[PDB]
Image (tube, rainbow, N blue to C red):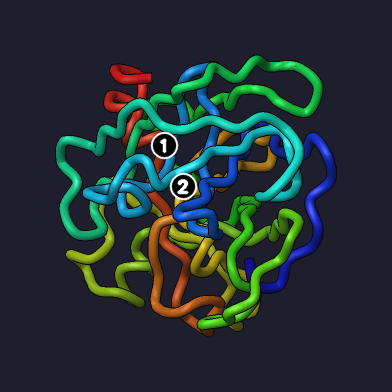
Amino acid sequence: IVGGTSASAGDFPFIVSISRNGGPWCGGSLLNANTVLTAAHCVSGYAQSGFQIRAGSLSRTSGGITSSLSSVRVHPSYSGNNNDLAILKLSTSIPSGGNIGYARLAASGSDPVAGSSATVAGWGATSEGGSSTPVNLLKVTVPIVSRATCRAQYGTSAITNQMFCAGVSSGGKDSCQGDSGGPIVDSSNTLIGAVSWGNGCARPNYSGVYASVGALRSFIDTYA
């Protein structure tokens, strides 16, 4: 996260860190005791055993409850950056309670309205290409950018009905590498997306692009 502040305990009861090979990699969202939602690109085709989920902590490396993966399922229409969601099943069930809880999801067919305030969180870099990452979870608030403006920035084909965008024109506030798969929420803390892609991080006039939970509820609901 670029331009962020430290998340408080319980800000995102459902957030998980996704380590790979013991190191930082992605974020995700705990949907139920047995299931994490993340970005497809975080997991597609990689060795499944390399991943470790941790819930209930502000750190990636201690606290809370861990699990390995039992299975990985990408969206059936995943292609390039499009439809960038995956369902992970956990080898260890994680109970809610305390600072762990399960996400509530954006309504099917909803689409975040331009100008509304969204909050994104993760353990990723704090600058584009930064090598160091924070121990504790960061968050930042950015407005939704209309799909039309996002298509002006990236091209018409590049931004689909299963993506939405968020950021500020001046840049300086965004998700970055290592934040992929983690949550973006609306002002009510309802999960509206997963961190997906963008042109660099926090650049002027290049929004962050998010996989849209509202657009992808059939897949989520079927397999969660």
- Mark 1 neighbour density, 10 Å: few (under 14) some (14–19) many (20 or more): many
Rendered residue at 41%/61% (across/down): 209
Q: Depth check: 55 or 8 in front?
A: 55
Residue 84 seen anywhere in this rendered image of the structure:
no
Q: Depth check: 206 or 24 in front?
A: 24
Q: Which quadrant: the N terminus?
A: bottom right
Q: To which residue does mark 2 refer? A: 194
Q: Where is residue 107 in the image (x, y as percent from the top left)?
A: 46, 26
Q: Position of residue 106 (x, y in %)?
A: 49, 30
Q: To which residue does mark 1 refer? A: 213
Instruction: Describe the element under mark 2 as helix, strand or loop.
Output: strand
Rendered residue at 64%/53% (across/down): 121
Q: Depth check: 50 or 5 in front?
A: 50
Identity, as a three-letter code, of the amino acid under mark 1: Val
Identity, as a three-letter code, of the amino acid under mark 2: Ala
Instruction: Describe the element under mark 1 as helix, strand or loop.
Output: loop
Checking the image for residue 114, the label placed there is none
